[PDB]
Image: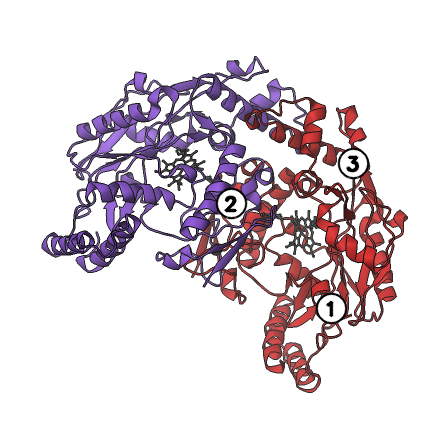
Chain colours: A purple, B red
Amino acid sequence: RFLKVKNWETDVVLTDTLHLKSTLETGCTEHICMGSIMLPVRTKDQLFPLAKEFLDQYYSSIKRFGSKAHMDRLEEVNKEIESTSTYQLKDTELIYGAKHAWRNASRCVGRIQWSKLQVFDARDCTTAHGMFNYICNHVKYATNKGNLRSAITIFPQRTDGKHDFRVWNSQLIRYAGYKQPDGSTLGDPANVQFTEICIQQGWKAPRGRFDVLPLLLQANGNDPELFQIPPELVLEVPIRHPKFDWFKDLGLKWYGLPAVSNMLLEIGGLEFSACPFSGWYMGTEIGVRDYCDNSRYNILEEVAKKMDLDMRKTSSLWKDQALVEINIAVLYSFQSDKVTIVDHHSATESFIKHMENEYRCRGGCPADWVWIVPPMSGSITPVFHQEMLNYRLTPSFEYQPDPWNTHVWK
Amino acid sequence: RFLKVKNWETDVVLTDTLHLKSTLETGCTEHICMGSIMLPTKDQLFPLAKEFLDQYYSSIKRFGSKAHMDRLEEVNKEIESTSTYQLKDTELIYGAKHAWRNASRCVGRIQWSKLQVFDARDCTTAHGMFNYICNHVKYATNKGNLRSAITIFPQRTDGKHDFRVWNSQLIRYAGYKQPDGSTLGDPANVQFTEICIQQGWKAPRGRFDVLPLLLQANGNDPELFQIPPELVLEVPIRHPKFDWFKDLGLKWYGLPAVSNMLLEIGGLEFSACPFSGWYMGTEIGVRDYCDNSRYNILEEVAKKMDLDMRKTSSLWKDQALVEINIAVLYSFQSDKVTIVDHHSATESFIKHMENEYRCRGGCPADWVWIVPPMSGSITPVFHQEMLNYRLTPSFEYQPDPWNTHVW
Ligand code: HEM
Ligand code: HEM
Ligand SMILES: C[C@H](O)[C@H](O)[C@H]1CNc2nc(N)[nH]c(=O)c2N1
Ligand SMILES: C[C@H](O)[C@H](O)[C@H]1CNc2nc(N)[nH]c(=O)c2N1
Ligand SMILES: CCCCNC(=N)NO
Ligand SMILES: CCCCNC(=N)NO
Ligand SMILES: [Zn+2]
């Protein structure tokens, strides 16, 4: 069954056959759509078919499907599974898998860049200190003095579920948050709970508005351990406005490396619970969400005041006005400091070309509209007008529960 | 079975059970979400009639009463004999209100119970429809103090005697593709604007010409009618700061009135049921004015604001967008014409969702349509999880008549 997707701004119609290979569930049914819902140890029994599916995709991608190399590998893996209950991926398969989990990430608007991904094989790591070293090298390589390079570091896969490797931080770089006795919060409200764990674990918090949190690393299922990322390795950008000279006095800055560290990478049925990855920011992640979400730095008012906007009634659109300036500032500061960043128009225009390319050469591109459309100026970006089909393909990146809610402390 | 919905800005969680009464499909499957797709017999009839009457009586606290049972049998017998039936005025009103209540893509449903219903089921001709429509327009406009309303024409019979309002909305501007290759007026209406032209209309070939109604009664060919200008309230768009704004020569009509949908109540289909509420500012300022396929006025407005349109990263399109929308709301409020900004409207919707969850056990909502076209995450609906499902009575999409009509 072929599915048609239309762009109501250009009438370009596309056909999707790719979804026919989808296997996982979406959370929706023929009676209800869960499209805006944020979150809707394997057995030998279930593992081999997952491995086969993967190795077939892999061997077909290199044009060796049916080859002896392909057949042998299938027998090798199969034997290994029956022999050990699991199996190890060749380096080539790991790189391929990692790149494809990104290619399949329907919530990611930056996928045009999917084939350019530096993969760091950290499967030989055994300790938290070991993890710390691998992560510092990832941060340095990735930051590349402001000229960002996409990368991912992959730690040992899950075995019995009692020896998981995990990066407790949700992102490698984020600012601490502190709940004050008067109910106010200093720093980033999103990280208050994690910040409490770090402090409890021994972190000496400077209790400021932009303190970089310490890495909290768990190796082989052991209790996690704290590590400070060398400051010289954390690239930061002071935020200022090209016209509003008072903007800088707002005392704002943000880090340049966005590195998701709490997701699970699944390849051939194998689970990589610690797989920190990074690209570069789209301006609105910082300017719209991090700075203006009511539950984050919530800076709209203050910026609103300084601009002396009519804040008496919402219909003045004072919030919308301050929002644009804040985002103008973030983009301005990053470009001035020569730190890679992409605006929402560029990013979405690019995703549109990527998507079209993918329908033609791949037969589709799963995409989650709800996440793809930028948090500001939605309809003046091309993705707003683009019908998208969302389905799950593997390899893929999945959510997993927070470690503090599952870990058995030793 | 009991689904939960979370608001990520406020941590509030609501439990949904209303979906368990859903009956129609969504377009999605366990393997694919089509949440962003724009358009995903006597025996058939009685069951629909029963589901409806059941909920109607339940709403009036007379569920399983004799009246309930009596009516169920009357309609029952009526279908067996007439292959259809007629709703009691009370049922018609209840149904229309609930079709609105069930409109998952409508953000202004907090207003759902206040709906003026005009029963035009006795209409028989295009002139009759024109009279009913002018009356609707006038009543709803109320000199600027808009009142929500719907006018319901005769239900479908054998499909060869359907009533239809060929316009997509009661009041729209015409569009004509010029020699230049460009488009004059509303690009969206070029096809309709032509069907009028070709049907007989004499276009003033302007940029904001109110289109003529094209009514179809009982299946006959449609006829043209020009709405009395004094009945079409318009608003000249000026900025509360940019005196030059006015020179753009922009204006918009005050009455938003969808006329191409189908109202389904207890199995019956009303193919001509124009309805209207009042505008949320972004509909005009963001979509009508700034869509590249509409009046596409960003550049012009950006130029007059003297912004660097060299690089997209200066966010000139964004800046202008904000001014344009500040103007729209400004004017409307200046001319005392009802309008609502996306902040106020979305805030209302959240409040309505909370009422619906605690009083009805849920509220179907299509996030893709509920979140405003600009400033998405600064409105509360952006952070609100929404479950979408189809309940009846409802408003459904239907084929444009000119692709089904046999002249
Ligand atoms: C090259 C630069 C890239 C850009 C500009 C880009 C941009 C984005 C943005 C704007 C989001 C939404 C983030 C949010 O709202 O929290 C996103 C999500 C995502 N990206 Fe990308 N991305 C890039 C690279 C990457 C890389 C390298 C990977 C994978 C190897 C990746 C995988 C994902 C995933 C899995 C999500 C959704 C995360 C979640 O569910 O929380 N992205 N991306
Ligand atoms: C009184 C204030 C009301 C407000 C502010 C409001 C606002 C909205 C908005 C912003 C949309 C999206 C329109 C678009 O983007 O095309 C919408 C759609 C819709 N509304 Fe409401 N509405 C109101 C009244 C009504 C009434 C009276 C009805 C019907 C009884 C209604 C039924 C619907 C339906 C079915 C849709 C979706 C139409 C489509 O799919 O094209 N609305 N409304
Ligand atoms: C493709 C996508 O479904 C389409 O652009 C939708 C998105 N959300 C919308 N939301 C509203 N209110 N109105 C629309 O016309 C749309 N268009
Ligand atoms: C409830 C709703 O799904 C939620 O607020 C989503 C919407 N779209 C999003 N899109 C992106 N890119 N990031 C987010 O965190 C969200 N949050
Ligand atoms: C770190 C924020 C979420 C993912 N965003 C991103 N731009 N990845 O590279
Ligand atoms: C007629 C435009 C779409 C519906 N909008 C509206 N505000 N209804 O009342
Ligand atoms: Zn869905």
Q: Give the residue at mark 2.
A: B384
Image point 69% across, 87% down: which residue? B81
Q: Is residue B153 visible?
A: yes
Image point 86% across, 55% down: which residue? B201
Image vertical order of residue A2 relative to residue A284, above or below: below
Numbered disc 2: what chain? B
* Front in this rendered view, residue B79 or A239: A239
**Is residue A384 found left or right of B260 in the rendered image?**
left
Image point 35% across, 56% down: which residue? A24
Q: Which mark is residue B377?
A: none
Q: Amino acid at mark 2?
A: Gln
Instruction: Please rate how many residues cluster around mark 1, counting C-alpha atoms within 10 Å: few if below 14, some from 14 to 19, many from 20.
Output: some
Numbered disc 3: what chain? B
Q: Give the residue at mark 3.
A: B250
Q: Are marks 2 and 1 on the same chain?
A: yes
Give the CA separation, mark 3 to mark 2.
35 Å
Instruction: Please rate how many residues cluster around mark 2, counting C-alpha atoms within 10 Å: few if below 14, some from 14 to 19, many from 20.
Output: many
